[PDB]
Image: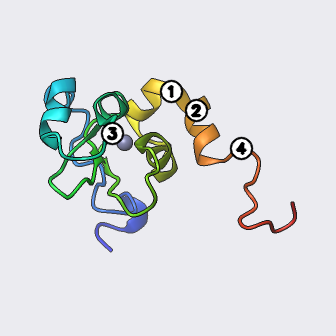
Amino acid sequence: MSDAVSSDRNFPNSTNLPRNPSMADYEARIFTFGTWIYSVNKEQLARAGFYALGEGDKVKCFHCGGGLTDWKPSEDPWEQHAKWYPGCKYLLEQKGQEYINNIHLTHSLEECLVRTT
Ligand SMILES: [Zn+2]
């Protein structure tokens, strides 16, 4: 439970000292991936604050302080990340909440299979 789930942060400090653009640079990110993961990752991640941790094609945010490994279809890091959590510093700094809001939510469905649409 830690120092009171309510008097702590519902977790052992998720943000592991993020906001480290010094090493999260452009060539720093791509460099991590050692040109192995999918294509279009250069601008994709470099712009969304995603860098390679060491898994096979997986990714995580180094500027926001959160992970987003591959466990679903191709799903561009842009869409996948925004759904993972809108409270990601850099992530928002790029396409603002207007985008993340459009992503996380949906185009109109938001019914899950159909429900009542
Ligand atoms: Zn993030």
Quadrant in which residue 112 is drawn = bottom right
Sequence order check, earlier mark of 4 and 2: 2
Kind of residue sitting beneath label 1: Lys
The secondary element bearing badge 1 is classed as helix
Q: Nearer the viewer, residue 18 or 73?
A: 73
Q: Residues within 10 Å of mark 2 (few under 14, many from 20)?
A: some
The secondary element bearing badge 4 is classed as loop
Asked if disc 1 and disc 2 are in contact, CB closer than 8 Å, the reply is: yes
**Picture residue at 33% right of the left edge, 74% below the top:** 1
Sequence order check, earlier mark of 1 and 4: 1
Q: Position of residue 101 (x, y in %)?
A: 61, 39
Q: Nearer the viewer, residue 106 or 34?
A: 34
Circle 1 residue:
95
Q: Residues within 10 Å of mark 1 (few under 14, many from 20)?
A: some
Circle 3 residue:
64
**Picture residue at 46% right of the left edge, 52% below the top:** 84
Circle 4 residue:
107
- The answer to whether residue 62 is left or right of residue 11 is left
The secondary element bearing badge 2 is classed as helix
Circle 2 residue:
99
Kind of residue sitting beneath label 3: Cys
Ligand 1 is found in the corner quadrant, namely top left
- The answer to whether residue 105 is left or right of residue 55 is right
Kind of residue sitting beneath label 4: His
Quadrant in which residue 4 is drawn = bottom left
Asked if disc 2 and disc 3 are in contact, CB closer than 8 Å, the reply is: no
